[PDB]
Each structure stands twice: as structure tokens, then as C-alpha cells.
Image: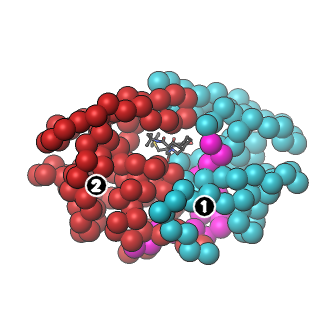
Chain colours: A cyan, B red
Amino acid sequence: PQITLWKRPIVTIRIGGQLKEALLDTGADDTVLEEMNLPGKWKPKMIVGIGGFVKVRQYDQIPIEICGHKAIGTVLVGPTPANIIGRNLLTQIGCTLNF
Amino acid sequence: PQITLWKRPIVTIRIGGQLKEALLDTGADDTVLEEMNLPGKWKPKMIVGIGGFVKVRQYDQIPIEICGHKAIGTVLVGPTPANIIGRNLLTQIGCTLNF
Ligand SMILES: Cc1c(O)cccc1C(=O)N[C@@H](CSc1ccccc1)[C@H](O)CN1C[C@H]2CCCC[C@H]2C[C@H]1C(=O)NC(C)(C)C
């Protein structure tokens, strides 16, 4: 698709058989989803947030479908105010910025 | 231009004789710049990021040149981790996400 920016670029994603809404986010390096359980081993991780670091859980090699495009990559889980899809997965689905 | 997302989408911006670098950020509603004195009336504002709120000054009708494109609109000024071009100006320059 082509997604304009008059409104927040939010799309439906599918992960672990669950459907969620997530923000296509070119200013984030990583993909961060709200608190949830995923299958497998995870590592503790700190990401740079407002007023300090935010603690998240890192899951690697997770299949995730983004607006019907398949990715397999790293998903961070934690207390984000919004589900965000970052560059690690935007590149996998062939997403560019254009003007 | 097409901008890929293998690295941070950073571009040169000009505002009023200042020449800075900033992220083209589809995840940001509004444009947020690091320390600079802009002319005109300001209004205090609190804006959400991961891990907390940043207190900013909101200025209206600020010209920024972005990759040779002329934008004019709201600019927020505060302790932001990075200079950010948000949707309010990204739309003005005709920026879309494509995949
Ligand atoms: C999540 C993430 C990573 O995993 C790695 C690197 C950066 C980020 C990251 O937080 N990126 C942000 C840019 S602000 C920024 C922060 C740190 C470094 C560079 C830029 C997002 O693109 C924007 N981010 C998207 C989104 C995040 C969840 C809360 C709602 C918005 C808030 C918005 C935001 O933070 N707003 C500002 C006021 C700071 C502009």
C-alpha cells in the first residue's frame, strides 16, 4: 500500500495468532509492543525513554504479519503507550519513505 | 526522493539561519526540536513518549526547510532525545510510506 500521514499510520498486525493495531514508526530503531506473553526465551533489555531507560523483554526471530506482509524478527515487549513497528521490521516488509 | 530505512532517516533542516539534523518520523504527531529560541508567542505543553512526558514550548507558524522543501507549521521545543520531523510537516512536503 501507500500510507499517507494526515492521520497516524496505524495498521493491523498478526502475532501469535493475535490481532493488534500498531503504529508504523520510522523514528524507532526497534519494534515495541504493549505487555503480552510470547512463546520462548527472552532477554531483559533497556531502551532509551523519556526521563530515563524503559525495561522491556526481547524476543528474537518472532514471526509477525504487518498489513499482510510477513516478517521474522526481534520484538520488544513492555510498557509502551502504543504498539510501534520500527525500522528492524519496516525494512523486512520493504517499507520506504517517499516524497 | 526515496528514503530507505536501513539507517535512521536523518536529513538536514534549516530554520531561520540554523542548520540542523532531524529524523523524518511517521510515529511523531508533531515536530519537536532541541533547544532553540523561536520568535512569537509560546504555549506550554506536555507530550507523550515511551516512559514519560516531555514538557515543551509550542510555537505556531514556523518555517523549516526540509530536503529543499518549504514547510510551515507548529514546532515544539523541549528536551527531546533527537530532533524530529513529525506528521504535521511530513504531510506538507508530500511524504508517504510505501510498501
Ligand atoms: C522506540 C525507539 C527505539 O526502540 C530506538 C530508538 C528510538 C525509539 C523512539 O522512541 N523513537 C521515537 C522518536 S524519539 C527518539 C528517541 C530515542 C532516540 C531517537 C529518537 C518515535 O519515533 C516517536 N514516538 C512514537 C510513539 C512511541 C510510543 C508513544 C507514542 C509515540 C511517541 C513518539 C515520541 O517519542 N514522541 C516525541 C515527543 C519524542 C517526538
Q: Seen in the image, is A82 located left or right of residue B53?
A: right
SS for callout 2:
strand
Q: Is residue A36 above or below residue A61?
A: above
Of B40 and B96, the residue lying toward us: B40
Residue A2 x/y as whole percent: 56, 74
Q: Which residue is mark 1?
A: A90
Three-letter residue code for mark 1: Leu
Residue range corresponding to the magenta coloring: A82-99
- Is B82 situated above or below A8? above
Q: Residue under label 2, please give it.
A: B73
In the rendered image, residue A91 lying in the magenta stretch gets the answer yes
Q: Quadrant of the C terminus of chain A?
A: bottom left
Q: Chain of mark 1?
A: A
From the top left corner, tell me how far across and down residue B36 is, in percent.
20, 38
Magenta stretch: residue B42 in it? no
Q: CA distance from mark 1 to mark 2?
A: 28 Å
- Secondary structure under tag 1 reads helix
Whether residue B75 is visible, yes or no, is yes
Q: Quadrant of residue B38?
A: top left
In the drawing, does residue A52 fall left or right of residue B92? Answer: right
Where is residue A23? Give x, y as percent.
Answer: 60, 53
